[PDB]
Each structure stands twice: as C-alpha cells, then as structure tokens.
Length: 226
RNA sequence: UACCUGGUUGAUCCUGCCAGUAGCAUAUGCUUGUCUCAAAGAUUAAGCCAUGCAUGUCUAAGUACGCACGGCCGGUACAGU
Image (cartoon, rainbow, N blue to C red):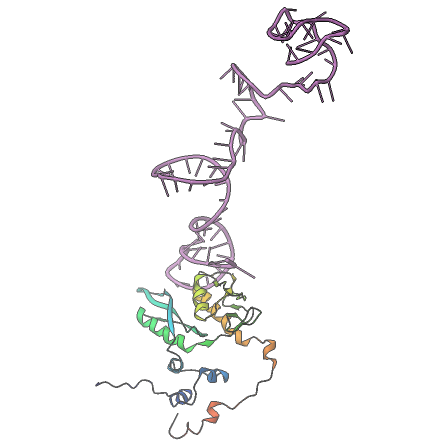
C-alpha cells in the first residue's frame, strides 16, 4: 500500500467511550436516553446492515425580485431489518449534496421498534406490540396488529418504512391528506416510535437501575480524553 | 390484500370536488386451434298475427245383428278379433 486511513476522531464524550470500546451496543445508549451528535457511532455498531431508500426529491422555491430561486429538498429513509429505522429530510441548492445531507441526518435520528405477537407465542415476533397511532399535521396512521402471513397492507409510502422496520404483518388506516407525503412519512415514523413508550402489563415488574456508562468508565474519560 | 395516486399556488399546509383504480351485467368493436358445463324477444309494444302442431282415453269384466274380417259347427243369452 501507500495510503492510510484515519477516519473519525470523536470530539464528543459519548463518541470517546465507543471509539475506545467500553460501550458495545446501542442498547446501552438508549437506556440512558443519551443524545447522539456524531453519525459514526451509529454506523459503527451498525452500518453493516443499513440501506437507504430515497423516497422523493421534491422542489421548493422562494421568490425574489430577480425571479425564482430553487432549492431541492429530498427525504431519505434508513434502516436495517433487525428493528432499527430512522428518517431525515434536508435541503440544499443542488441535488446530490441534498441526498447525501439527508443520509447523514437520517442516521442521527435512528430509534428502535418493539415487536410482539398476535395473541399466541411461538417465538420470533412478527407484528406491532399493540394498536397505536401517530399524527403529523392532520395525517395519521393507525397501526393495528395482524396474524401471520397477511403481509403489510398499506399504501406504497408507509409500506417502505414498515418493511424496513422488519414488521412483517400489519393493517393500517389513514385519515386526511396523504398526497403531501412529507407529513405522511413522518406520521408513520411517529407511530413506530411510540411502541416502547406504551406501557403494558408485562413491564409492570420493577427495573433495577444501574449507574451510567459515563459514571462507571469516568476513569478512562479523564487521562487526556474528552 | 382492513391500501390509495394525479390536479387550485411563485412556494407551503388544509378544506373539497373532479379524474385515475377493481369487480359485477347489458350492449358493441376487433380477433379466435381443441375440450367440458350452458344463459338466450324480460327491459321497448300484457302490441298484432299467416301456416303447422301443443288432450285424449278400453280390460276376461258397461253396450257389438259394421251387411268389416273370421269361422267349420254353430247359436241354445252366446265366440274370436
């Protein structure tokens, strides 16, 4: 060879524990609900199963005395089929740059989904935990559980997101405008997010509590480290 | 298969209709090699009709002098068909 690599040097505390390798799953991060700020952290644990699916590339434009001025705004989905999905929108003066700007922003906003069973257990979840909703500006979706082998029955736009989530079988119902897909996709994304925030009788058992990764590994975060 | 997509603006988010989509049954266009199943003058004029046909029927057992046939030998109630 004659060419090295050097990629990523964290300037963030959370980034430093991952690069020095003390955190070894996303599940640690999420349990303390820490901010994520660097898009390499997510792409280190994953990035070996993340795909992108560019939904729309939509023009928008404002008005000035010299005429039109046009910016391109594109939406880009991201997700592995193991239950982590995310979504981002971004705009720029040119097309390709806006797409690549959206793939970064989408990595940042990745969240987990909680899957469950129709009513009888047989191992390996296949549907949504419970009947949930999510609204974004008078578009809404109502993800309703479904038995095995019925597939995802939805419009083409949410059929992307739910498929990327790894949710196998679902029924949906929409209300209001859905031709303004920027709302429609965010409303789907809203619905899948709420799954872990829905309290179920399962979760009534008490959580132990444990000290933060920041707390326990603080001796490695002070030597010269950020 | 518990589903949507295009269109009011310089641009955005709504309200709302229009158009797109699929099945079903009537008509119609164009095209048609083999097999099984088969709906068919209802929609309008319960308007009008040539011609042909669509309800007849006898057992040992209601009535046989058909001069019909037959008999064989006829008639005494009197054969058989």
